[PDB]
Amino acid sequence: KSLYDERKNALSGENTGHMSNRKKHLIQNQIKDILVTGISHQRAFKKTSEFISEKSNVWNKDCGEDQIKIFLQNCVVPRVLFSPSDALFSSFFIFMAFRTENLMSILNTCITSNILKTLLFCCTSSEAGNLGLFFTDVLKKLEKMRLNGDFNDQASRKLYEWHSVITEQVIDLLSEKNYMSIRNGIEFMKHVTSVFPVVKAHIQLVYTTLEENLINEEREDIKLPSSALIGHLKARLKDALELDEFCTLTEEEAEQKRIREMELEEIKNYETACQNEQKQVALRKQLELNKSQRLQ
Amino acid sequence: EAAQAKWESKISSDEIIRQWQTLRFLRSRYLFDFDKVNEKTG
Amino acid sequence: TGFKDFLLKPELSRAIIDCGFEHPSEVQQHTIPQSIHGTDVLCQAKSGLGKTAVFVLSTLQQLDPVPGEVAVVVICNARELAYQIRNEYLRFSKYMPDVKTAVFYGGTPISKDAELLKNKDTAPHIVVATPGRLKALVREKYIDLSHVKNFVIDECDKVLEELDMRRDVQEIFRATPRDKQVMMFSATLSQEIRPICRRFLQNPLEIFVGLQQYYIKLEEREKNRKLAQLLDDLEFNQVIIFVKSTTRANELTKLLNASNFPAITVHGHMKQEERIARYKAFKDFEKRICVSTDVFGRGIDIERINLAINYDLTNEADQYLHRVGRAGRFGTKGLAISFVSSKEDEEVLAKIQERFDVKIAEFPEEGIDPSTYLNN
Amino acid sequence: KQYARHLIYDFRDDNSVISSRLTSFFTDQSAISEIILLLYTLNLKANTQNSHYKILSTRCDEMNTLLWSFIELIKHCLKG
């Protein structure tokens, strides 16, 4: 309803004066023409909302894992790889038709199954760009219901676990061969970079991988989006990012946090004063070390 | 099914761009397996 | 589309396809996507190689539309170039109805421009000016510079050098917040001005830097008759005629306008206001024939010219490469015809074929083929 | 929807007469069901030709948005 009202704010705020009678005749004809359209679109939405609500009760009486796999590939995926206005439908349908427990079980097999490095290999520049518009509207609806809406801590562990497998799928895609894997992964990362920042660490995983393919080889002029994605990736590094307020299950990662606290407290007095000289390895060098530990 | 009959014959016994055109055909029904069933995804 | 590979806003990437650009320059390759992040830039590059395309695309992504507050400030060298910045800022923003851009320069009443900025229907988010004018607005409480986030200094070496043009650029920098982004570009950056220019920037990024040719072997008086033979034989898009004087250059167009070839004249010894408008109509396809002296030898990019005839041949090989560098732009075919009429002329081409390794062959008596410079 | 095409520069309400005359030459020879089957077949036949590697990632995309562009001309002219 909000985009209907601001259209009326355009004509009322811009045109304030005497220019002609025919020009102000046609505007007041249109200010009622939008309102008859909005209440009929409301009645069209009212016709479908109680229709989908009375349908979904006998729909969400049976949940399947193999009965949902054929739905995800023969009814969901070809309507994402078709059109950008049509890929917005495939996200709006899952968050409206299925219920809350059904929604998580659908998005389970979509992400943990490593197919996202395989779809983005065999697409076009537009088909790969429409796949990114799917996961933009999925993660935007998940981040809004985690901030405003409340979750249990066991569910919020599963939400941040999906972010761990998303970032390790795209990095394996970028380290592949010449052109088809690299160019699609850039355009896929162009749209999902809006709601990226869930964890400070995961931004630095996807950032330095663009530097590994930058120094060694330059086949075509693909350094230009690589520097452009770098300028967008680090632009959200400084807002609010810490995995220790929300993810609280820390049985060992608290210990590797507790070691890293004593390395920074030792080195902050080493840069202030000088009593016993001891050198350590910096962040990005040891942040380069755990890449090849996971790349193998 | 002939593309899988082409597939099941060679397992019993460029091409990566020939792999690019097969994977635009096999994403119709046999999509959710895609680990190592046809080839090495590399 | 090479400019969607800048990973820009979808609204900004629409008009670039309507602007015709597809390949980025080497100056645009190195300093735009790092200017998106918000750090300052320091650039040196050749003139006319896409220096102005850096700062237009960089500022339209950064601006948030606010009603009645300015957000982009461009300071420049003269009144002429500021009108060229305005025409390119609107072209990439033809599909944004909220943004607006106005131009400020001398010769215009300031209080009448004060009615332009106070009225909200012409109160823009982007203001470009020469600092000779933009100093005069703030000293009477007309505009406010407290909501600006981007600052652009084009031709930073030529503005900061003169002490009278140094005082007006300093007060606007004091009338704006220093927590800001400052952009500085120029064509010639020497080692003397670069310690002077680093006062405005915080952690900046530094950047420092066929054709078929033929000649006619003829005597002195056959080439005013060879003019009307080479015109009515060749099928030309637009032709340029190069005369090494200003006395012969004005006698020719009065001869051509009565021979039913409409033409214009642009060179020196004339008003500079006439030199802009007469060169504009030649780009506007108003007429297809123009004569000119050695002013238009170097640097002019009009791609519709494919026939360049030399009425009076050069004495060197370093002026001749510039006059025929206009025809046949970017892989297009063209023609270069020279009138040899003196004794020093034959020695010029004898050093050309040994330096540039180009064989200026002899003009055939039967004429050239029509399918070697159109099809081939 | 008529405002969203005015901003994207998609003129359909202006040249509605000239667009109906163009499909009148397609429906006189009964060519409308022939074009849709021919653009789809040639796009699917271009999945076996071996010319280059970056070329057929753009040629397949360009013929895909031609078939989408002809369907959208049919629904605006043959209305009813």
Image (cartoon, coloured by chain):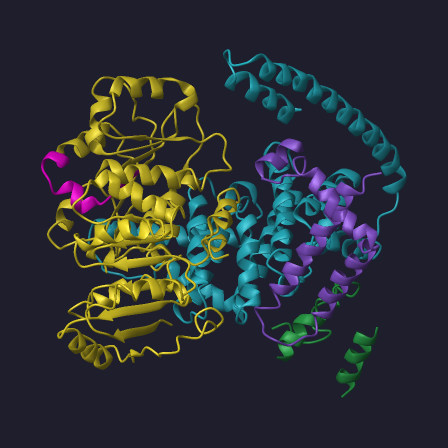
Chain colours: A cyan, B green, C yellow, D purple
Q: How many marks?
A: 0
Residue C264, image x and y in percent? 30, 48
Magenta stretch: residue C158 in it? yes
Rendering quarter of residue C298 = bottom left
State the residue at coordinates (79%, 75%).
B3
Position of C121 compared to D9: left or right?
left
Above or below, A68 against C129 in this view is below
Is residue A152 or residue A14 the one in the foreground? A14
Is residue C336 or residue A242 the one in the foreground? C336
Residue C193, image x and y in percent? 13, 49
Q: Residue furthest bottom?
A: B13
Magenta stretch: residue A296 in it? no
Magenta part of the protein: which range?
C151-166
Q: Residue furthest right?
A: A58
Position of D35 compared to A263: left or right?
right
Is there any visible trace of residue C76 in the rendered image? no
Residue C119, image x and y in percent? 39, 17
